[PDB]
Image (cartoon, rainbow, N blue to C red):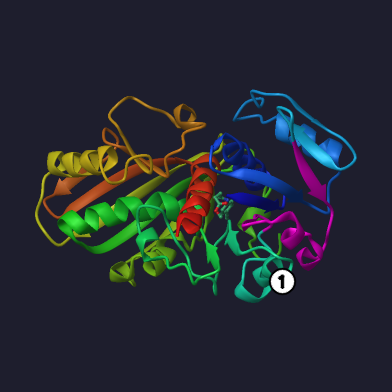
Amino acid sequence: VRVAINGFGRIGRLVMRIALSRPNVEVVALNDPFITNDYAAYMFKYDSTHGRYAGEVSHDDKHIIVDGKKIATYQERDPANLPWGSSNVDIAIDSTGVFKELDTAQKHIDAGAKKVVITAPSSTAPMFVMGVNEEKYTSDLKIVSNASCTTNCLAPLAKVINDAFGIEEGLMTTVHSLTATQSHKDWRGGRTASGNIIPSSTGAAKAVGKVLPELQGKLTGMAFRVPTVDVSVVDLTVKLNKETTYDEIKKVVKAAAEGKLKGVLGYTEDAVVSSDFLGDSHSSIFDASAGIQLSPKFVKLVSWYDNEYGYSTRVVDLVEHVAKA
Ligand SMILES: *[C@H](CC(=O)Nc1ccc(C#C)cc1)C(=O)OC
């Protein structure tokens, strides 16, 4: 599968690291009008949290070069100008977060790509979360969104819990890290991040309603942003339809993690802390020891996620899936 990446922020760079390692995915091109090839190579080589790339990185006037593989580079403000038809780009991965609707992501189709994968939530493109609703994709949909990293953490765990015990209602808190610098629409967010706990909204709990229609209207929540490494944790307080015990929840989650959700949902019982998940490619790692059940239908469930790395692995997953179709 021949892919091109638009945008070389955190996500585009990690999607590229992962796609270089996928045997059936070939990275053909990169586009980003705001950086030069030498900065792109620097940014790709170094990462404060996910380590130096274990391989050789350089560049020339027309490529970024990774372990010898030359990857053509472009600087187009308008993706309609990119040579995707000429380059034979099967799937364009858009990680700019600005061409994230059906009419704007269309530009990659116009430029010659067969399909587009938006690495950001979308109001108009269909949204897919691996292990939740990817079986619902059909090969006539040409533009799709991988939702958000918090949605990717919550939705697999919510699906498992709802399938086994039913969710009547749930309230979610995410203790959310500073990913990168991501302030006149959000006053709390313009305060110094570095020493503060900063409450914030989130649409993650409601976007689960898109990929799990049966949970529509049954979840909401909020976030506390903290100044830690790029690993966050979801704190899900659910009212259940059916009585259960915490050991039963553990077995159900563990079975899904070892079975149908292998590689997407993880499971631990160790005395973990957030930095133990830097680089973890799961969407959601259930922390069995951190959760707590009060009564047979009322439980707090806890799940970790590297908010860049698991998401970016799911992106390349969705790319292969959309291609396998
Ligand atoms: C996952 C990474 C991420 O969570 N970025 C993020 C989201 C919300 C806020 C706020 C307020 C800050 C940073 C991702 O990129 O999904 C879109």
**Relative to residue 160, is residue 285 drawn left or right?**
right
Among the 4 quarters of the image, the one containing residue 213: bottom left
Residue drawn at (72%, 24%) of the image: 56
Q: Residue at x 48, y 53 (%)?
A: 318
In the picture, the quarter occupied by the C terminus is bottom left
| Residue in front for this viewpoint, 310 or 233 | 310
Looking at this rendering, what residue extends furthest in the right direction? 61
> Relative to 54, is 211 above or below?
below
Within 10 Å of disc 1 (Cα), the crowding (few <14, some 14-19, many 20+) is some
Q: Position of residue 132 (x, y in %)?
A: 35, 57
Q: Which residues are magenta?
A: 70-96
Whether 94 is among the magenta residues is: yes
**Left or right for 150, reference 291:** right
Asked if residue 195 is among those painted magenta in the image, a careful observer would answer no
Percent x, y of residue 291: 27, 40
* Residue 179 visible within the image: no
Foreground: 224 or 105? 105
* Residue 207 visible in this rendered orientation of the protein: yes
Q: Where is residue 228? Give x, y as percent.
A: 55, 35
Q: Position of residue 304 (x, y in %)?
A: 41, 40
Report the label total: 1
The quarter of the displayed image where residue 165 is located: bottom left
**Residue 291, above or below 298:** above
Residue under the image location 31 percent in, 25 percent down: 270
* Foreground of the two, 284 or 128: 128
Check disc 1 and report the residue beneath it. 110
15 vs 62, left or right, is left
Q: Amino acid at mark 1?
A: Asp
The residue that appears at 57% across and 49% down in the rendered structure is 1
Secondary structure at numbered mark 1: helix
